Image (tube, rainbow, N blue to C red):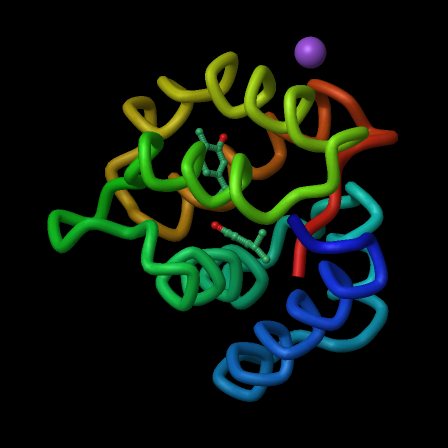
Length: 123
Ligand SMILES: Cc1ccc(C(C)C)cc1O
Ligand SMILES: Cc1ccc(C(C)C)cc1O
Ligand code: NA
């Protein structure tokens, strides 16, 4: 799996690909990585772009939870891995409450952060 430094480098590259498509500032993006979620549609759709870049958005506009779990297994350092997977399982039905795909990814991500803020990270 990646080290935490490598994981951050990977997340930074995903941010650098997706952030230009949305009216999202460093304050908004750093806050999001830190588990603070501005209620801003541009930030919600940024989270969907990140899920799309990870290849975890199906073409129906839903989150592929099994693919997300397989990525965390492969990529996350062990102090993060089992906790991230338990968070993902816990939050797997949040997306069913939202019609809009940017809502699905934003609120699913916020569920992961609330599950354990010390483990949580996001691009
Ligand atoms: C949404 C999302 C962000 C980062 C990663 C990797 C960098 C662990 C996977 C993923 O599915
Ligand atoms: C179940 C579930 C999958 C992916 C994500 C994020 C990583 C997009 C959150 C979540 O709660
Ligand atoms: Na856990």
